[PDB]
Length: 6
Image (cartoon, rainbow, N blue to C red; front, side, top):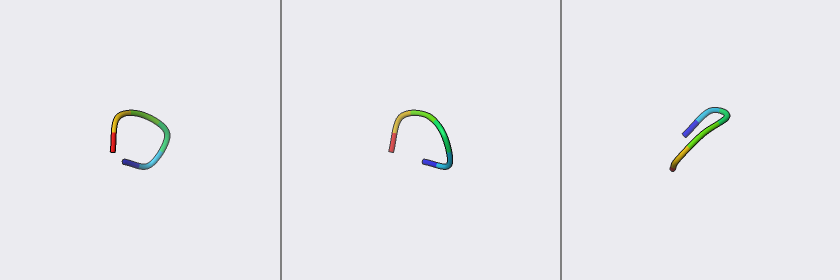
């Protein structure tokens, strides 16, 4: 995601 995991 966005700035982390996925």
